[PDB]
């Protein structure tokens, strides 16, 4: 951290803070994650795995600096996040061709991770980073399985996590991404819950309370209660107007209760919704 020159704070999580920084040596402008340890060797070997997980839609981990018994992560810097971009686009909304490019690119990023059995676990607009070339990238990626388990947002949590499933799958990333998709389209968060039960109950209201019919094995989940209220499902035409039939078809399959019926990243990339996919460049004000 002697080689770096903190420019401004650009982010924060549970494991540390992130600074835009300039490499005193090399002129390089980077995003530097200062990991707050209180060292663990298992955590080190895990992070070093992430140096190999390289993809155009994953924020590039440049270096891992383990020194003075502190850990720093040096990433590629991107000039904006999707939250700020969505906020800046909220009067007219993000154009659908741009929505579709970003969904396809993130689905490409996830197909890759997931093919390597790596899950993200916390996809949200603030973890999606955009550049001036029309690229979108997954950030803060696999840095949860490392050390183990600010108000953390629950809005993009898959239902199996909220129901206490301890061994959840890559399908939790598709759910989160589905929620992000919906939010880009409608310009409102799909499931803005302010606690786990409020989050779960907001999902139940929209998609219906899950049962053995739509989700075999659900009544046997750790935090499942026979006493959960029994809401009927609403139509998707009400949930994401004015998303077209292809978009709403894909979204429904990304929001299946059953994690084994939920569409994979690979299958989603073949969905008719991306027949006409392009790569627009956004208009970014930095
Ligand atoms: C609001 O305008 C913004 C401008 C730039 C960023 C920005 N943030 C980052 C960032 N990290 C902060 C955002 C992603 N979140 C995290 O990395 C956390 C929190 N989940 C710290 C682990 C990384 Br890495 C690379 N380029 C970045 N660019 C964010 C917002």
Image: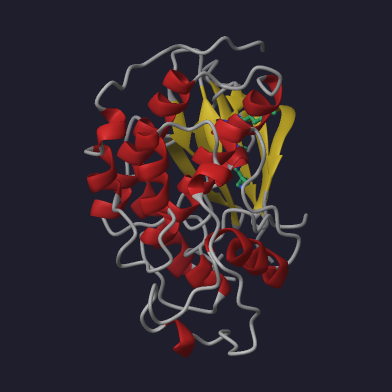
Q: Quadrant of ligand 1?
A: top right
Q: In this rendering, does residue 65 appear at all?
A: no
Residue 118: x and y, percent?
Answer: 34, 57
Residue drawn at point x = 30 percent, y = 67 percent: 260
For the residue pair 173 and 237, the one nearer the viewer reads as: 237
Residue drawn at point x = 34 percent, y = 54 percent: 49
- The C terminus, quarter of image: top right
Q: Is residue 126 above or below residue 114?
A: above
Horizontal side, residue 16 vs residue 62: left or right: right
Q: Is residue 153 above or below residue 2?
A: below
For the residue pair 233 and 197, the one nearer the viewer reads as: 233
Quadrant of residue 82 within the rendered picture: top right
Quadrant of residue 198 within the rendered picture: bottom right
Horizontal side, residue 96 vs residue 13: left or right: left
Q: In this rendering, does residue 100 appear at all?
A: yes
For the residue pair 61 and 120, the one nearer the viewer reads as: 120
Residue drawn at point x = 42 percent, y = 19 percent: 97
Q: Is residue 212 above or below residue 261?
A: below
- The N terminus, quarter of image: top right
Residue 15: x and y, percent?
Answer: 64, 56
Colouring rule applied to residues: secondary structure
Q: Is residue 170 above or below residue 138?
A: below
Callout count:
0
Residue 35: x and y, percent?
Answer: 63, 52
Residue 146: x and y, percent?
Answer: 48, 63
């Amino acid at each position: 951290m002697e080689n770096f020159q903190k420019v401004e704070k650009i982010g924060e999580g549970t494991y540390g803070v992130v600074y835009k920084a300039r490499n005193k040596l090399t002129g390089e402008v980077v995003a530097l994650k200062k990991i707050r340890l209180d060292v663990p060797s298992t955590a080190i070997r895990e992070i070093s795995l992430l140096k190999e997980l390289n993809h155009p839609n994953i924020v590039k981990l440049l270096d891992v600096i383990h020194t003075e018994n502190k850990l720093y992560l040096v990433f590629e810097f991107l000039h904006q996040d999707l939250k700020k971009f969505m906020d800046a686009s909220a009067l007219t909304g993000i154009p659908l061709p741009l929505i579709k490019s970003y969904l396809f690119q993130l689905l490409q990023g996830l197909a890759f991770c997931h093919s390597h059995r790596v899950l993200h676990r916390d996809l949200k607009p603030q973890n999606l980073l955009i550049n001036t070339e029309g690229a979108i990238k997954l950030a803060d990626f696999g840095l949860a399985r490392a050390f183990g388990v600010e108000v953390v947002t629950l809005w993009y949590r898959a239902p199996e996590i909220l129901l206490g499933c301890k061994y959840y799958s890559t399908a939790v990333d598709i759910w989160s991404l589905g929620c992000i998709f919906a939010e880009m389209v409608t310009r409102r968060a799909l499931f803005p819950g302010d606690s786990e039960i409020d989050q779960l109950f907001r999902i139940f209201r929209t998609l219906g309370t899950p049962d053995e019919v739509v989700w075999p094995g659900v009544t046997s989940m750790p935090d499942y209660k026979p006493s959960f209220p029994k809401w009927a499902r609403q139509d998707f035409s009400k949930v994401v107007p004015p998303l077209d039939e292809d978009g709403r078809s894909l979204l429904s399959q990304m929001l299946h209760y059953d994690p084994n019926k939920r569409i994979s990243a690979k299958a989603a990339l073949a969905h008719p919704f991306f027949q006409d996919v392009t790569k627009p460049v956004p208009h970014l004000r930095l």
